Image (cartoon, rainbow over all chains, first blue to last red; front, side, top):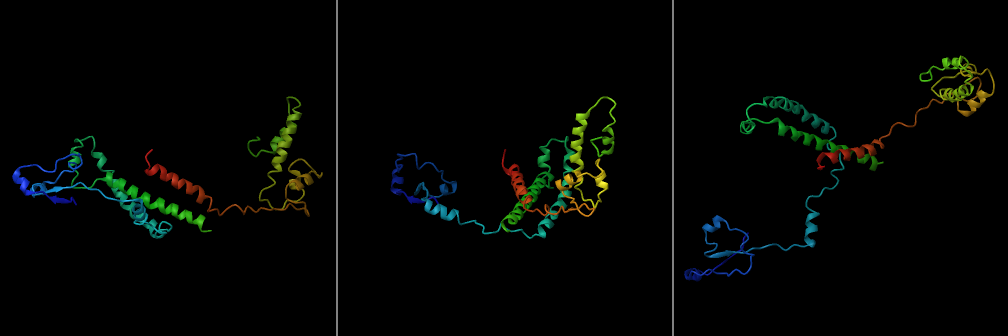
Length: 154
Length: 116
């Protein structure tokens, strides 16, 4: 945003530096080199700003933007949840075979070469712990949400 | 022999003492197996007449079978011990795993993302 305003070019001819700083409040944000190419100062100046908000506005936009309705009280495609629970594990086997591959070239060339050298082909380590999180969060949520409705509904 | 289902051999040891009297100990030994036979009448048996389980303890025909037969079931009938082998009420419990497992799921979620 950075609201600016003109400075007198007459005072530029005077060689006199304007605006007479009495408070350490304006020299806090550093101007860009691209606006420094332009006449931000030689012809204009920056102003430090903020914003005015209140609890009248904070709650009525916090409590309203991303809000579910009854969505977590469902079963999430009850035939296909367990189908997906194999649709990840099946290639997780072969990725665990890559985890049965990449550990075996350790105690070798130093691992900084194992940092540069692995920029063409995938690692089993990060990709492995990814699907652990995916399969975990896909299961425990549907598990607990399945079991509340037994209590609540009769 | 009291450890396994050796009953008859224990009651053979009731009277076969070479050492001394042991009378007060084989009388406790008598009561503590009296309620044990009186316990193992309570299976899924069929009709037993008034001779077989009448003679499994040590009696011919006193009213001690009236004491056990009115103590527990297997009711005094026409030469009959009645089998109430029901074992029906307790299964089909979804709600108890839906409380205990409802605890253990969140307890799985505690040591899953929150730092300890």
